[PDB]
Amino acid sequence: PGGVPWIAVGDETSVTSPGALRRMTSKDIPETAIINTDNSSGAVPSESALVPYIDEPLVVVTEHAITNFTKAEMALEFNREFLDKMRVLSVSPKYSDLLTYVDCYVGVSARQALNNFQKQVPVITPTRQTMYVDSIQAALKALEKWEIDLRVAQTLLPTNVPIGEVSCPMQSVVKLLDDQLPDDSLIRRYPKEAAVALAKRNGGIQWMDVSEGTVMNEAVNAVAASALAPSASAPPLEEKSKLTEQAMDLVTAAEPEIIASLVPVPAPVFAIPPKPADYNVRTLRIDEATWLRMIPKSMNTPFQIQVTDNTGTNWHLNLRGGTRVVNLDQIAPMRFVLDLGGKSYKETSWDPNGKKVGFIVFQSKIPFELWTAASQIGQATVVNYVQLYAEDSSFTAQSIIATTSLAYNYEPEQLNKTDPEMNYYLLATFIDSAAITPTNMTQPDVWDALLTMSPLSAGEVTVKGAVVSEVVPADLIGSYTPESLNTSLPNDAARCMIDRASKIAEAIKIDDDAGPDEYSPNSVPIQGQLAISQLETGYGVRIFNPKGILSKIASRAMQAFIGDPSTIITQAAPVLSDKNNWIALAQGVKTSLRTKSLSAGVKTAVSKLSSSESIQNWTQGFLDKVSAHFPAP
Amino acid sequence: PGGVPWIAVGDETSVTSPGALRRMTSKDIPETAIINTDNSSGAVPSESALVPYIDEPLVVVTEHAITNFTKAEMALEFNREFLDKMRVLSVSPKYSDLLTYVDCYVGVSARQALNNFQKQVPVITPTRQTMYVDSIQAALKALEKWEIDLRVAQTLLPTNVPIGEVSCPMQSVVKLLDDQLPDDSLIRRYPKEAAVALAKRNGGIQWMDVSEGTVMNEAVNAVAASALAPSASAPPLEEKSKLTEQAMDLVTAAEPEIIASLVPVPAPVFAIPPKPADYNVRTLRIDEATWLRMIPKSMNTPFQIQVTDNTGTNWHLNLRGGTRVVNLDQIAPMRFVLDLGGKSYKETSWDPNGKKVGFIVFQSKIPFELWTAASQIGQATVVNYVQLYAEDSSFTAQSIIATTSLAYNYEPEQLNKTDPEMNYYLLATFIDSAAITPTNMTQPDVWDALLTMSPLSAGEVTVKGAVVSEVVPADLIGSYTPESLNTSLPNDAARCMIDRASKIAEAIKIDDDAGPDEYSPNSVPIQGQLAISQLETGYGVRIFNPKGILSKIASRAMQAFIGDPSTIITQAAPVLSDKNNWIALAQGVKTSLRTKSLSAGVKTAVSKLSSSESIQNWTQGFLDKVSAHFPAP
């Protein structure tokens, strides 16, 4: 049943009673007290001075429990011949001898025990338990180095054949092990023990008995090894159970009820651990990356400003048309690592070497692109900076900046944006103490490098470059242009949904061994979602088609999904763009995987035996070599 | 008890029995049917063909129905002698006689009635109970003119006195009735019916009987009169058990636990119906009223823009420095109504008469402070406009503009706020069909007016001209300047803290009767907070003051709170600036009322008495005038 035994003190209490039950202890059951535990293996100190005599509680043991603590005992008992050599655990534990039975009220809380009066409930003290588990693990610790030697013996040459059977003279095989087992092995010390230890765990390996001249099968797990056997027709039962589980282990952890939701869904339950993303800021098309800002080009204006850092060091820099900043608002607190290294940045009178670059945060009410003077920038700070080095590269007659790792990360906490009229801008540019001539340096920024972007808030997701509290996974399907997707933020909705939906794809592969252009238990749900869409009364030019074609289209379309999951959100993909196609896929994945009955696909069934029979030939191939180079009298 | 009777069908059920019971019906107890009902008053017809012959549900009648429904009957019998004169209702209904005492499982639910079983329970059907009040109620209509003419007889001359007794010959007083009662009064027709009627409800009025030649008291409500009658030294009980009632009732409405909350509190629960406010935009200090936006001086330029109306009509209106607008953002929709009567707006080349003014709404990303051009208004629409009339005023030789009602109700769901850097502005200026010379009219705006803010919300509370969904009543104390209030919006937290604390302010006065510079149970919770504060060492110079000083300071301050409820949101209020003083007062009123024992103030107790015998003294002299001018033979 489970829980803890109880005793009744009310003497007139039946159910739902104030003070009916109390805990059972060792004064209630004197036997369940640690002086009456058998001193087998010498666990309890016999000398009377060291025994506590203080009461201890009682816990109920379930069936499955003893079913495992008994099983754990046999970990020792494969190696018993070796244990006796080590003079340890002479008498086996026998878990059940540690048990004890009462028929008293059983339960976790007394309210539940009050009506649970079982019979012959096994019981044990917590201290007697700890006396047991350590004993097993004690011997397991003792057998460690012996264990490795047994494995290296078995794995030196094939002791198991996947399918069928093989044969080889014994004197030949032991001799080949003589010169390859390490000298410091305990097979060297104790052969006769190892020999019977092997034969307990392999039906093939036997040992004829010199007494009566008899040889026999000795292994103990005969019932186990059957389920691991290919038949004349299909693979072993074991993995055929396993595989369909792992498919359901994925479809479960990918929680399809979310990725199918046609309703507003909060961001955190939909977000997953995102991945870093990479960009080259200069090269972007501005009309796409909606999270960028750019001071307009071609006005001739150009000026200088001075901004300090946390230390207060005053600097100088330029701003000019064409310069770009990121709009720090709603950038879903993020991280910036920019590597200027590998570019030239050399002017006719401005060498990049020696100068400094850095990040510059901004605060100014006027929108960024309307900046035209030093007055309106308002509040600004320099958060980080480095000093550059330049190196000559393969392209002869030039030099090239060495590696940089300008770091910075964004956190809304410090900024504390409460004024609904505030603006926030980040920018990487040359920085120096002295002023810069407006024409002696002519770059608009230094954003012409490699930018690696990494998220910090995994509980908040942007969509189309804009943060949002909730998302609707249904409506994302078939709404992205690959121009846009490359310019997406690393913690975008699709990013979390592309790989999450990819997680569905592995299941389909692990279940579907279908080739090109034929139906499949997971390609067919699309097919139904196609036929009915045809038959309705609608726009355009209607078209009928026989099911011979309709069936292929789904299979042709599904093969895309495993081939690339990201294509479903790509705009106007032939089949997967539509949502009704998408949903009908994400339910069959659940249902098909729940109706399989210990089966592999026809093509997987046929191939695996043939791949298996091929190996068995190679096993006799190796064994036949063992004999010729190690004969027998 | 109460609820519904239930009859049994299984007879073998104890608890959680699914359907053991069944709703009893009038057929099961055929005494509760309308063919057996006592037809006293003759309500139900007496012809078989005109009778429902259909059963009805049963409802249980509880103690408090019987005590009151019957008690309602007696209010009829106070006027029996006229009812009978009208030959109606010869037999009084006797509510209880329409019941039948049964014993069954009774309860609102069959579940709860399952174990709730009773004995001799009153039962009635709805139709029977409906008819009973109809019998009562139709008589109250019958006495629709009698009772009015009854009261005027009592109210024409003082029949009741607050204290003591008075006297006047009955011969005289009746003679005063005859010449001052309307000829149509029912008492003119039926003198003796009135005479018995008044004697039942007034002990003083007692009639001699010619047979026995005796006379005695007659009133039927002597116990009731003993509640409203004062003692020779104490006020009446009823009006005391009535005052403490009001005071508690006001506090429970004021919800002291909110206005004493030390942590954040949501807005819609906190706020209550607001009152319209008024401001003078031209006269507010632009720094104080943060909900204002205005163009700097010193630009030297001036420009005109075209804006369309909802009807597509186009209009021209000019702009300059100091032209104030209002930030429609963080306003929690208001009603903007504008009046112009009483101003001049007359210029050397601009006669305001005949022109038009209107509210113009702006939508731009560009912040209003940095406008200079006509291409950066953004989106505009003349949301409303009205014509102008002019008349001459007390100032000789110049006219004045007449009443205007230019109104617009701000409503954010129209604005469709979607851009975090978008901006909204509202203007009030002149509008003309064609262009207007920027020079001949040099008013920056018409914002010199009497604008009335009317809130369109109660769940939305602004603070310091800015909205917030979370208010902390503790921190509103000592945080408003005498100016900052006069810049706030009507839907402010303070005006919500004020108009609520007034009821707490009003609550005190009904109980408390202190005066100048003496303590009270309600001024004392302040005083407890003062001793401990000065006792602990603070900052500056520690000073010491005996308790006599503290006692006055608390009462004086509590007078100041009663004098002006709005004294606690101020800044630097001498005593009430601190929350601990405010908090302790808040919790102290609840105790001070619940711990009264039918008590009343000590000074008032004398005053109530002393005032009353003056009323008696006045009354007697007035009765004397009756005998002087209606002398009995």
Image: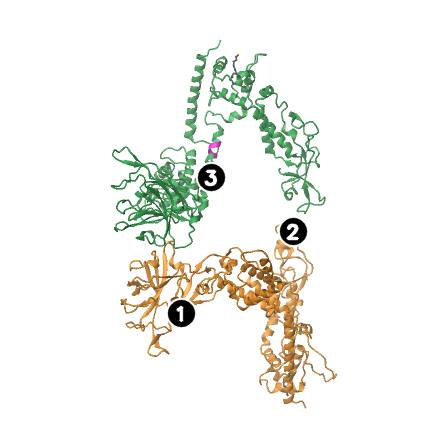
Chain colours: A green, B orange
Alpha carbons under labels 3 and 2: distance apart: 52 Å
User: Which residue is label 2 attached to?
Assistant: B10
Give coordinates of residue B371: x percent, y percent. Answer: 32, 59
The circle drawn on residue B395 is none
The residues colored magenta run A241-245
Q: Is residue B22 left or right of residue B422?
A: right
Alpha carbons under labels 3 and 1: distance apart: 65 Å
The secondary structure type at the circle numbered 2 is loop
Q: Quadrant of the N terminus of chain B?
A: bottom right
Check chain identity for marks 3 and 2: say if they share one. no
Q: Residues within 10 Å of mark 1 (few under 14, many from 20)?
A: some
Q: Is residue A20 left or right of residue A182?
A: right
* Residue furthest to the right: B212
Check chain identity for marks 3 and 1: say if they share one. no
Q: Nearer the viewer, residue B109 or A61?
A: A61
User: Which residue is label 3 attached to?
Assistant: A253
Q: Chain of mark 3?
A: A
Q: Chain of mark 1?
A: B
Residue B483 vs A42, above or below: the answer is below
Give coordinates of residue B501: x percent, y percent. Answer: 53, 64
State if disc 1 and disc 3 touch (CB < 8 Å). no
Q: Earlier in the sequence, mark 2 or mark 1?
A: 2
Give coordinates of residue B49: x percent, y percent. Answer: 59, 68
Q: Which-is-in-front pick, marks 3 and 1?
A: 1
Residue A496 vs B478, above or below: the answer is above
Alpha carbons under labels 2 and 1: distance apart: 79 Å
User: Which residue is label 1 attached to?
Assistant: B450
